Image (tube, rainbow, N blue to C red; front, side, top):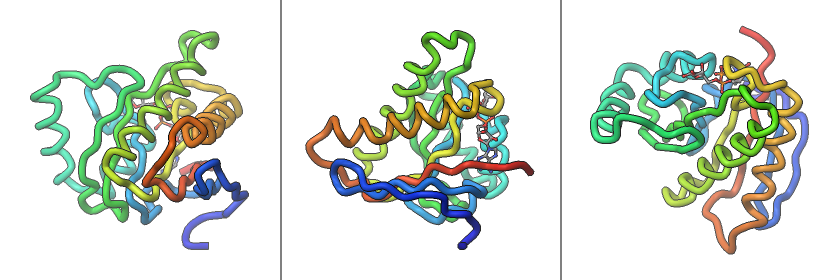
Length: 176
Ligand SMILES: Nc1ncnc2c1ncn2[C@@H]1O[C@H](COP(=O)(O)OP(=O)(O)OC[C@H]2O[C@@H](O)[C@H](O)[C@@H]2O)[C@@H](O)[C@H]1O
């Protein structure tokens, strides 16, 4: 349906709808998609390559301007650029944590999700789509990533009084 298998739906604390779906993040037409990247904001990751192909060269200039001013996106932190030719309006870039330390990696992933949602909310983003951050090149076990991200999303809306965000999509991905 519209590029995706729709697996489940849940209502969150402030009336958000959380969908778990399976498909290609870059085919989501919403306000923002979330790009798991590193401190240089490259598109070298698995998702990142697909985002860069769908967005086109325009996205490069915005990333370059940001990196020219800031030099680094710190781990777990987020930054936003236009999505250019992507179906989605914005890209929320997050410096994805590595699964170097199972004992602290889930805390870092939780914080990454919360930082992405926080930043999206300041931009009045209404719909946002997350891939399984960390579980590709950064080696999170898939089930630990899913559980941690889904719990982080629910907890974010438990922790605030108001939000512009109305739907969150968690996008699972099978293979190329
Ligand atoms: N088009 C896609 N849509 C949705 N999910 C996808 C897609 N393509 C791959 N995935 C899945 O997204 C998840 C994250 O994979 P990565 O893109 O490799 O992200 P991550 O594990 O967070 O590593 C970040 C990567 O970016 C680099 O700059 C950094 O050094 C690291 O290599 C994986 O489960 C992967 O199967």
